[PDB]
Amino acid sequence: YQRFEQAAAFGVIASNANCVWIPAPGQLITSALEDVNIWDIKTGDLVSKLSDGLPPGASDARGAKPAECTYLEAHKDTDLLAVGYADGVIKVWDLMSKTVLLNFNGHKAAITLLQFDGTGTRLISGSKDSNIIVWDLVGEVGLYKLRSHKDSITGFWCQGEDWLISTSKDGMIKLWDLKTHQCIETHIAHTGECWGLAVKDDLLITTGTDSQVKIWKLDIENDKMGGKLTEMGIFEKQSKQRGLKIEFITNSSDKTSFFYIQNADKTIETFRIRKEEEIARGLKKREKRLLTEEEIAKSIYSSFILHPFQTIRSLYKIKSASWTTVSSSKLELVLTTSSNTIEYYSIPYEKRDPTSPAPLKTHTIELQGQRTDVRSIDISDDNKLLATASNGSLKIWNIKTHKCIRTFECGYALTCKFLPGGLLVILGTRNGELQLFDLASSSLLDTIEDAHDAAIWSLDLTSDGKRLVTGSADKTVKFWDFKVLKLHHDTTLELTDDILCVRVSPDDRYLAISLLDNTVKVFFLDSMKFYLSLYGHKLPVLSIDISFDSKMIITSSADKNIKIWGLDFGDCHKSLFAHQDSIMNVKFLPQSHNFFSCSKDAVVKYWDGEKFECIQKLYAHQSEVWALAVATDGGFVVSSSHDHSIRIWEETSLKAGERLMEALDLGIAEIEGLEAYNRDMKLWQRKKLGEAPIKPQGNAVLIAVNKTPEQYIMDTLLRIRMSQLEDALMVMPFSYVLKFLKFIDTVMQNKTLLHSHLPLICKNLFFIIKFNHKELVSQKNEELKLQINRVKTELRSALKSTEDDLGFNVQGLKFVKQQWNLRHNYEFVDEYDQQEKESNSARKRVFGTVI
Amino acid sequence: NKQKQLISCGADGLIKCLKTLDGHNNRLWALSTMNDGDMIVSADADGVFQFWKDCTEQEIEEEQEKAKLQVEQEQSLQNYMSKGDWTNAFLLAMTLDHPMRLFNVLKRALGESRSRQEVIFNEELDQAISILNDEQLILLMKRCRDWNTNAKTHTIAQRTIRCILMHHNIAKLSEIPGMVKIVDAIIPYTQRHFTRVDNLVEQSYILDYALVEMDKLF
Amino acid sequence: YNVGKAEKDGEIRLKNGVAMSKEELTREDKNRLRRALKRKRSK
RNA sequence: CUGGGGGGAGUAUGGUCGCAAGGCUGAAACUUAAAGGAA
């Protein structure tokens, strides 16, 4: 088969991520969906779209959504870009050659921050799941995983090798000793979430849910447990929403610091922090009226040391920001907003006055976007493309360059079409209005106010183009002719129900209209004849398509399935269930019975109309695919979605016993090696110090598991099971029994792991010598005789030491119970009433017996 | 202030349902709530009055101050489990009531007590277990009771029972309400552990029999 | 006396004897103890 | 306020006249949604 693929994607400038700024104002790296694009603020031309080397839609593209980029981060000097994606992976690229250097999957959810540290070679990464991982770049390895937060890492701040400090989407800020990787000090920052973190070395600043911004003093050289990071006071903002990024600078040329808190909505609150001279010369002024009350006033600091500044607003909702500074009169701040647009503002400040009632944007890159989701896409014969938006941004892109060359202002517009000669656009809007535009001249040929009483929903030209059909939510369809280049309403068909799709056949034959009442009706255009009524879809029914032979129609709806109908008798053929949310649009190919359907769950799907298979399952969008349009000839198809994207699609095993034996042999070899080393040390310290042994290096596996040999043998002796322990001890020969006795003799000098394994040592040792008693008492060596005596003394001392406190506790606890009894048990002198009282007050337990 | 409301004379003022107030000893013809927003609520019985405080936001600050305290001194116990110094770790795990961390501080302090060298822990730890009150020692003996049911974890329980017995007053231990259903529960466990360790030390003398055979060898 | 279940709700008390507190268990042991309780319910 | 078939208790029915089964519903021209049932 001649399958499909993706040629190019565009329409996005700023997506659901952050932005990094690079100096030459300068350029900007930001996110498109799953690929990063670089822009020069000066002009705004797309100078780079760094993308994955595999086209989404190819043979090896995997069966899921692609990983949306979610955090840009840049190493300036050594020229790297660490970008991180929605599944958790981190790709590190060199910006010179634009290839992938490092892949750093690691995480389990989406990631939320990156940071290079010690400028090169180290990258720390925080994610939706509460881990935060340190990575080395000269080893390609996750070094450390700091794991104690609970919800989602909202920010952190590190210095090199000793201290990190993170704050997460619970209420908690944490300080991490990066030598031990244990959390040192934990506070509750804000009572809900904690969304911000910034610090200029003395003061730390955090923000939470609503306007309460908290100043902290971190004293890194502190020694107390609670008090490495203390809280110094709160203050307020003007926004009651989530401040979610704070960032600082030190402008030179005096020395000064500025920080911003961007908000959820539309607003960045900028702040100047002042200097120690005006701290000292402002302290007395609030210390006026002359001291317990004045000390309470001086303690209740934030408004003192912090100074608000020019509160920069924007048109849309703010997603990310970053700035640069010179002279303290060029706080030059780039800002990517949600409705895709970047904006380069710059506030001046004459070091006492900010010299403006409201700041000024110096650049704005917004030409290659829409600011809303494209509710309708269209195409020329083959050359141009039509994108229809809610703000009014009709845009005429071109296929061969992916640049909008022509754009207008219409309104909440949901459907549009071209006109068959090209260079002319019809369009209908949300309210009762229709509009006409062109390509060479300006916007409005004419608008028709009161084109319909209510929301228009779908229009269609005839194949010659002179006559178009508009169906609207005022329960009417209308017909319009082109009189000479103006619209002529002549007839109108009022239905009982809100018509929401129209279509004609591609040979002027049928008019199929989709009603809100779960059905479609097929009419004859030449008679308004009411040929057919296709029924049985069971929810209101979206896009129709008529085939090129005018024999076969498709019918999409919000029932998550498309139905194929034969138009000769109105008989159904398939009812194939696609698309688990809602099929928004469905369109045939030009010459074939193959078709495409794009849906509300971020997927387009390629089907055939003969076997009714799914030919292909294309997976490049991220959100609700609102429209798609096929070429008139040739058959390449464009699809446009809710993530502001427009994309083209073209054609192409030991056991117990022997484990204990090998553990015993290496353990006792290490043990008597160290004992020979100690005898060598005593002889070369008691004799002429001219020589000694060189070095016994400790065993590989013993230093690899970090265990003394007694502990190594002790845990493998633990790890054999009780059912095969009497076999594990019976398999081993008498030489291993003798070195087992050496092992027990050494282990009851370390009285820590003697007392934690007393019954195990007793059981194993007594079975060993009880089984090997005949040979043991025939061995003739005073070393083993002294060994047995030493083991006997230390073992029996440990056992009598534990049963001493056992017997003590028995007699003490029964004394306690008995003195409680003789204090207040009861008063019976008569033995029969006494025994009946004790029988009524006894402990009962009921048992299931068999008779 | 919009929608919840006060009613009177169950024997008490009640708000809308939640928060039965203190009330009185008998009946009631009284409500005056009408200062600034909804300030001081006078509610009067036959003779006795109450002047109910303010907007009820005082409790939430107190309510939000404990969780902060508990999450602060939960990240002191982890630092103590890291670096040792088991005494404040012990009393603070007793305050938090973290039972397996309590078993860990007692077990590792007991192991190092076996290591180095009247006193059975370090002396600052057993005076710290000497100076704890009735609720703490009764929950300490609840979980010494349930640790004593093992044959592995029983030694830590026996030595904690031993230091309680030799650092507290025995009449006080009897008069604490609840500590006669615990000691009845873990006397017979100590009895079976005594019989088991006595059987183990009586079958320990095959080493001595092997020594006398090895001496009769020559 | 035999070790039943805990008389609190932030506590997990196995019949071994080892009482664990839910505030002191990490999330790995929380998932592991939940699956183990699911096994002991399912049998 | 005159008009009457033929005992009681049962049994069978290859006759005639009826009433009645199936089998998840939605759901067929469509192997089709939501939701419900059952286990």
Image: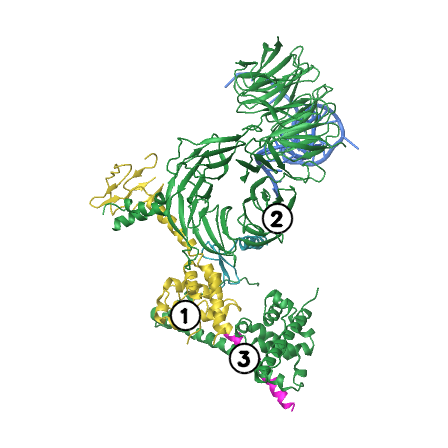
**Viewer-closest of C38 and B113:** B113
Instruction: Determine which residue is flagged by label 1.
Output: B126
**Quadrant position of residue B161:** bottom left
In the image, is residue B209 part of the stretch drawn in magenta? yes
Q: Amino acid at mark 2?
A: Phe
Callouts 1 and 3 on one subunit? no
Chain in green, by letter, is A
Q: For this view, does A656 lie left or right of residue A844?
A: right
Q: What chain is the yellow one?
A: B
Q: Which residue in the rendered view is the most extreme toward the bottom?
A: B218
How many marks the image carries: the answer is 3
In the image, A540 versus A63, the foreground residue is A63
From this viewpoint, is residue A729 visible? yes
Q: Nearer the viewer, mark 2 or mark 1?
A: 2
- Please state the chain letter of the residue tagged with numbered disc 2 in the rendered image: A
Tell me which segment is drawn in magenta.
B194-218
Letter of the chain shown blue in the rendering = D
Determine the CA span between mark 2 and mark 3.
Answer: 55 Å
Amino acid under disc 3: Glu
Q: What secondary structure prevails in the magenta region?
A: helix
Residue B155 percent across, percent down from the top left:
49, 70
For chain C, the rendered hue is cyan
Q: How is the image coloured?
A: by chain
Label 1, secondary structure: give it. Answer: helix
In the image, A351 versus B55, the foreground residue is: A351
In the displayed structure, B72 sits above or below A389; it is below
Quarter placement of the C terminus of chain A: bottom right
* Percent x, y of residue B46: 21, 44
Q: Which residue is mark 2?
A: A104
Label 3 element class: helix
Subunit that carries the residue with mark 1: B
Instruction: Check disc 3 and report the residue beneath it.
Output: A794
